[PDB]
Amino acid sequence: MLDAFAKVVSQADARGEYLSGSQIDALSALVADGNKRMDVVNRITGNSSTIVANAARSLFAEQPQLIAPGGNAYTSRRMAACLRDMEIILRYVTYAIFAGDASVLDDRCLNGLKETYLALGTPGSSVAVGVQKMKDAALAIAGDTNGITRGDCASLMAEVASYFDKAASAVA
Amino acid sequence: MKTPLTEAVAAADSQGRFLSSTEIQTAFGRFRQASASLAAAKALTEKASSLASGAANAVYSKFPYTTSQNGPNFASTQTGKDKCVRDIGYYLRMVTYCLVVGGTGPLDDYLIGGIAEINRTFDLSPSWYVEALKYIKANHGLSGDPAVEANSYIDYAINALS
Ligand SMILES: *[C@@H](C)[C@H]1/C(=C/c2[nH]c(/C=C3N=C(/C=C4\NC(=O)C(CC)=C4C)C(C)=C\3CCC(=O)O)c(CCC(=O)O)c2C)NC(=O)[C@@H]1C
Ligand SMILES: *[C@H](C)[C@H]1/C(=C/c2[nH]c(/C=C3N=C(/C=C4\NC(=O)C(CC)=C4C)C(C)=C\3CCC(=O)O)c(CCC(=O)O)c2C)NC(=O)[C@@H]1C
Ligand SMILES: *[C@H](C)[C@H]1/C(=C/c2[nH]c(/C=C3N=C(/C=C4\NC(=O)C(CC)=C4C)C(C)=C\3CCC(=O)O)c(CCC(=O)O)c2C)NC(=O)[C@@H]1C
Image (cartoon, rainbow over all chains, first blue to last red; front, side, top):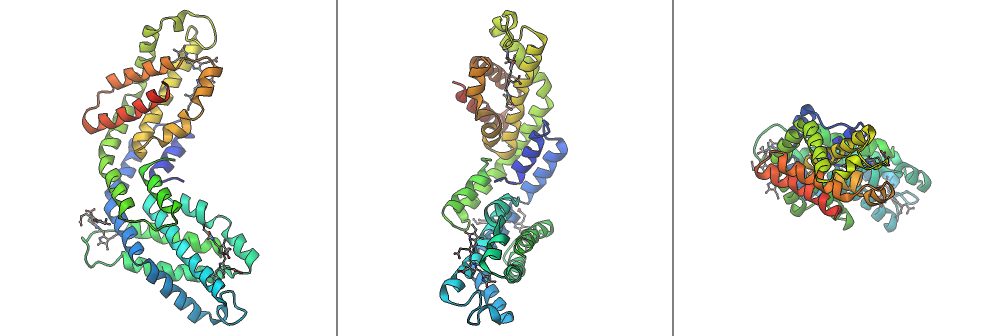
């Protein structure tokens, strides 16, 4: 896997170059947002159970056929698998946010997901609604201006939303 | 690639865990070190042409056979001399990468893994590179944290060769 730093280096090595002063400044800007990124990782992690539960509760309320008998999330083993999948996808979103690169999410998590559900009979597009409901909740917990030093997190917030969006467009 | 952040993520993933304050304190250590690392990366890069050429010359003085002995592995020809400074410029460029990510990952991945096989097949002596790397360390002109952490990576290369 790569982080935001490694990613730049690996695109430079393939060209045989040293990083430019420009590239170095941009990575400095990333280091400048270091604490803010860790507050996002900390916050979503600290509420991870609640984000998962509340997301699944709202999915099953909107989409009652997944839980009716015969539904892909009917029976305890299937329900347990579904909540497990939601927790896994959140965990690897928080990895990508920590490292400031999507490698780990694509490589370890998303890769081959859509074909797994296709083989299983699991409705990918319902999986994607679940991911979206976890997105809104997480952006709201990470953006809470209480009990933190005020500042601007707007790029970070954009970067986070993209990793969820990358998860949702993968399975759907 | 091995960096403090991909190490921390790998440990959590290996245990199927979310990240904890443990892994955050690793990010905190990396982000605070990154000023000296990056300031060192900029410095080496500014000098890179001249350190590489000076380091090649330092080898050719320590080991004058390398310029007078016959055979494609020696710098007794124009191509050999070009190949030699090209090689040293690769070591130096890897060490700047290592500064940028804060760990040995670029060295391991691009340079160190395999190098024994290459040195034996092409009959290149490790001792030529250890000499070039001791020059670089004596001449890069860094001080303080920048120098301590650049030297760390140069000494890692040296120890992989010895
Ligand atoms: C956007 C994400 C929000 C935001 C973030 C923000 N935080 C800081 C400052 C810091 N955050 C921390 C983080 C931690 N300290 C710890 O001990 C732990 C647990 C192990 C964590 C995760 C730290 C150390 C700081 C700096 C010290 C401080 O408390 O200020 C800032 C200020 C900028 C800075 O980096 O110093 C900002 C802007 N602020 C918001 O308004 C968004 C909701
Ligand atoms: C919940 C939102 C939805 C749902 C999910 C569902 N998933 C499974 C089965 C699998 N899910 C995975 C996915 C992964 N496993 C991993 O280890 C990783 C990351 C490293 C991922 C993303 C896999 C591989 C399976 C198959 C293995 C297994 O079932 O344990 C099920 C079970 C299907 C079954 O027939 O048992 C279910 C139910 N179901 C829905 O209805 C929701 C939309
Ligand atoms: C300089 C200190 C001495 C020296 C140099 C010399 N090197 C070669 C040839 C090779 N060097 C490499 C090494 C690398 N290639 C890589 O991709 C990497 C990591 C990114 C490194 C460090 C390789 C693979 C070769 C062989 C293939 C090639 O030619 O590129 C030669 C030529 C040897 C030959 O037999 O053709 C020479 C001359 N020689 C000296 O005498 C100097 C003291």
